[PDB]
Length: 398
Ligand SMILES: [Cl-]
Ligand SMILES: [Cl-]
Ligand SMILES: [Cl-]
Ligand SMILES: [Cl-]
Ligand SMILES: [Cl-]
Ligand SMILES: [Cl-]
Ligand SMILES: [Cl-]
Image (tube, rainbow, N blue to C red; front, side, top):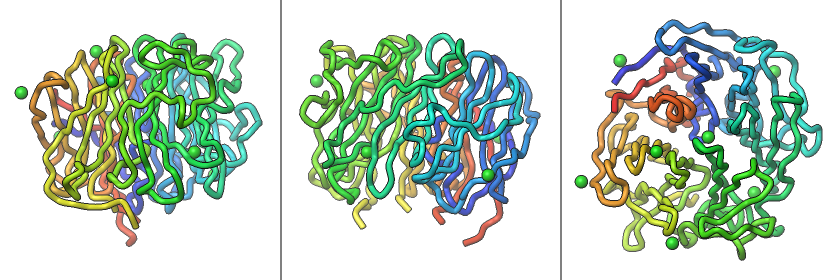
């Protein structure tokens, strides 16, 4: 299992290593790009040729509040090769920059997208759309308010426009926590859990929608077009799960080449106090679930979480499931099923060392285009002032 050194980065919190960095690492053509905060809090951008281990690294003019692990960096490359990057939010005005030129690590000034509803941003996420355009998703609101906002970047006009103002409706009652993926056919997939009130134990259910027209209209797997916005009552339930089953929020999802969705998360068995890793997927006709490992060690979300929220990639039913577990010494770990429906899941460790509070993020585009799995790997703590730890790209042997 081959580790490619990048550079040392901040490790006192998990800001560089959350599951919801979309993306920390991204390939365009034969170049791979990475982003992180250095030990002084500066946003660093880097790139290499995929056939080299020599990085060009550039400390930008920007800093982030790295003591708040919410305040992540998400990046993406558009069809003309410009880096788009958004960073350093926890209910704050939008921070968004772009490369000054194709493939450049140098950024211009902070810019608006649409200039509307950009005062209270959390969780910036980018996804590439067919033809070179980009999608941007974020949570708008402070003091417990949350709403999913979705924009599109037209490569042609070089501008952002709003796609949905209200896609998921909490009806002034509840919040949602979501994840998305744009499949190899350009379909946008969306899944989420509800959170009924302040407390994490009030998370419940896994819901799903998809769009074939870059976010304008939305469908269920069973073919019905949604009447928007999507509420508790009309949502498609991929998996019905109660409150108080240790169901976690804000994980990740993927799809196979055929456009079938796969969702990776965790929750406990009814007759147990031990959360277990899960996969939920739809085969075109039915939703299924499987438990990935047989953990022994209990924990509860109520009141550092001992396991990481997961990532997955899929190849025609074959699943590679990336996680981290105190039971395995907090190494980077992988579970593999030849066939998601029927195989036993074989577990291996991808690092021989602990990465502690690390969660996985991966080069989504390299998997889609080249079927290679590269992970952003760095030891971090749930913040003790520790020395910055080396960031690697882990090039996975499968
Ligand atoms: Cl190595
Ligand atoms: Cl700054
Ligand atoms: Cl929300
Ligand atoms: Cl994607
Ligand atoms: Cl596939
Ligand atoms: Cl079903
Ligand atoms: Cl088997």
